[PDB]
Image (cartoon, rainbow, N blue to C red):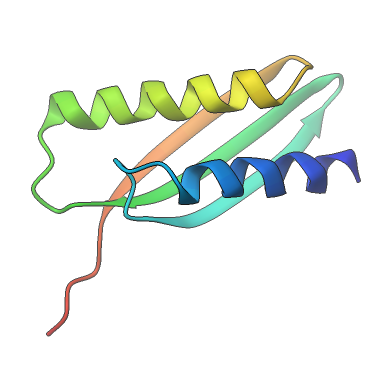
Length: 84
């Protein structure tokens, strides 16, 4: 349940993080005392590899700051969906 509190705050931040177009999905589970996060994000289709690595680092910083306990963070980046 404190798990849902963390997810909500994480989503609130990510929504306001300009390098991220949208949150695709946030999953969390407990592995003993470790919280495991899987974060899927939409980003601009033209990002470079370096920018993508820099966004994963920002996401990781956000989680580490919000969650007091030990965590693992896996981030996946997807091209934002463009209008047809």
